Amino acid sequence: LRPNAVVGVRLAALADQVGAALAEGPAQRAVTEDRTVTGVTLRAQDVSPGDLFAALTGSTTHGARHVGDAIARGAVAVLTDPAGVAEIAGRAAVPVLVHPAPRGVLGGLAATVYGHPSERLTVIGITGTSGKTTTTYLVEAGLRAAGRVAGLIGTIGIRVGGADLPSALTTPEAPTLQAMLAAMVERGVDTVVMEVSSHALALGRVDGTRFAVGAFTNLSRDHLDFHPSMADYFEAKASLFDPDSALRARTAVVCIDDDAGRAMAARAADAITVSAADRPAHWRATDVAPTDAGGQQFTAIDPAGVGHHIGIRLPGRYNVANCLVALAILDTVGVSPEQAVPGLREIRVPGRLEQIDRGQGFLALVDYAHKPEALRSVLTTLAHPDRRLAVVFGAGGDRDPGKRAPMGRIAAQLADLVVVTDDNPRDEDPTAIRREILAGAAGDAQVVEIADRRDAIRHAVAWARPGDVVLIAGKGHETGQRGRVRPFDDRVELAAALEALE
Ligand SMILES: CC(=O)N[C@H]1[C@@H](OP(=O)(O)OP(=O)(O)OC[C@H]2O[C@@H](n3ccc(=O)[nH]c3=O)[C@H](O)[C@@H]2O)O[C@H](CO)[C@@H](O)[C@@H]1O[C@H](C)C(=O)N[C@@H](C)C(=O)N[C@H](CCC(=O)O)C(=O)O
Ligand SMILES: Nc1ncnc2c1ncn2[C@@H]1O[C@H](COP(=O)(O)OP(=O)(O)O)[C@@H](O)[C@H]1O
Ligand SMILES: [Mg+2]
Ligand SMILES: [Mg+2]
């Protein structure tokens, strides 16, 4: 939610803090001494009375052009850039604070009006190319097993303890974040575990937030259509670990298995390191054993050299690594592996190598892997000689068209059966999309095009023999087929197909 009980901030105080100016005149600085701001939003439609409207520029528009609407919703002030005041021109009924780079000071403003919620919460922020969602779930399940009230914030949604709101973004815009945090304080939450996307660091979405811990899972080619370079992409994320940085967390935890990880550990200087790949780390895993129920058990050796028999419901070598990160994260936040192990044992994180096992025979999995790097890593962790691997997936219309032809190649290379299907074709004639992935497909593999997604799932389930694996890729927890939005859920379709087998 927003929080029910916020004591406001005199608008004068917000202005002096940020050091904004007043669009009308320096003497408009009499009525600013008067108004109280009790909310902050950067989406006109979302203003409550008493809120400061942040009118920002963006790639599609400028919020300055929605001042009318914000004011009409009872906004008591606007905070905008000079490009913005130009848009307003004359005449808003309310005061206009002007900053260069407002987005870059919005966080701290929001943090102030909401009374600095992060200073009352142990906030854990997990960044990295992959594994943020999974690691957050593992941390959250540890937390609950040890009887701590926990909020979660990430791709899948928001959890205020037991509550279960859905999220638009993986990390919400700074006023939303702070207000959520504020609400979590009111709701009795003690600890909050957060995915922190590299977009959020770039656009200063997490600006007013104090982190008790920052975790780094890994890095690989992603988001290179927002970040202008792999550098910037690293740099964004680094800003959570750099000792001297503004966002630096009280404790950093870094996985060492990736090269990028090594590079972050060296950045954070006093990182707690973590390795599932026989690398020297404070936390290390060994004796990794596949188990019946497609889980994995292993020994987690802590920074004190003490072993711990752990058991995780998720397949794939790197999930041992996620688990370690989570394990380290809990330990620093004062939760021992003894306390967390029961939670970890059971936790199934949705759309992430989620195994459906209605019936028996082979491994049937649902996974979110939707980018060429994503897909390669999964298929490899799931490849074993003497076992067959089917992958079914497709690509999204109006979305990054470069990624299609690569994926089909990666698929062809690592799977025994690939099935090319629809996954939100949107406006585009769906057979183009599929035909591009199949261009990718151009010995080992065996590839076929089934346009209908349920039919794709069914064919692959009828193709499996005992002990083989079927992976439904590229939707994960996401639902619906957009084309209208037709209703679709991969877990449900997958389970349905397995029942149809006898
Ligand atoms: C690229 C990016 O970060 N974009 C975000 C950005 O949009 P941007 O400022 O152009 O927005 P704009 O529409 O052109 O105008 C700027 C401001 O005008 C204001 N506005 C606009 C229209 C209106 O009617 N009223 C209004 O107030 C909006 O509040 C807007 O924030 O500001 C908006 C909110 O501040 C977001 O909608 C938008 O994210 C869109 C939804 C998005 O797709 N973001 C994705 C790409 C993203 O952020 N992804 C990562 C996760 C990646 C992962 O999980 O691997 C994430 O954290 O979500
Ligand atoms: N440590 C990891 N390394 C590589 N791939 C991973 C890792 N953890 C999870 N994955 C896979 O990558 C995809 C996205 O990971 P997820 O757990 O949703 O984290 P994120 O929020 O970082 O995307 C999933 O399909 C998942 O199975
Ligand atoms: Mg990402
Ligand atoms: Mg995520």
Image (cartoon, rainbow, N blue to C red):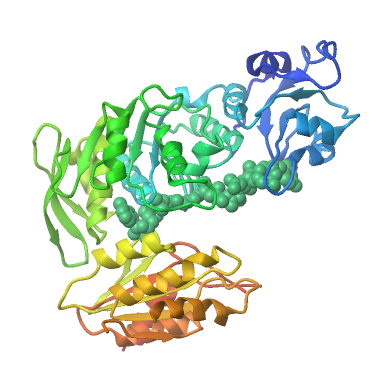
The reply, left or right, for residue 257 in relation to residue 209 is: left
The image quadrant of residue 4 is top right
What residue occupies the far right of the structure in this picture?
90
The image quadrant of residue 392 is bottom left
Instruction: Identify the image quadrant of the C terminus.
Output: bottom left
Q: Nearer the viewer, residue 110 or 380?
A: 380
**Identity of the residue drawn at 75% across and 40% down:** 63
Q: Is residue 468 above or below residue 121?
A: below
Residue 438 percent location from the top left of the image: 44, 80
Residue 192 percent location from the top left of the image: 42, 36
Q: Is residue 391 above or below residue 98?
A: below
Residue 429 percent location from the top left of the image: 62, 79
Q: Is residue 169 visible?
A: no
Residue 79 percent location from the top left of the image: 73, 28
Number of callouts in the render? 0
Q: Nearer the viewer, residue 169 or 371?
A: 371
Instruction: Identify the image quadrant of the N terminus.
Output: top right
**Identity of the residue drawn at 24% across and 37% down:** 328
Q: Is residue 78 visible?
A: yes
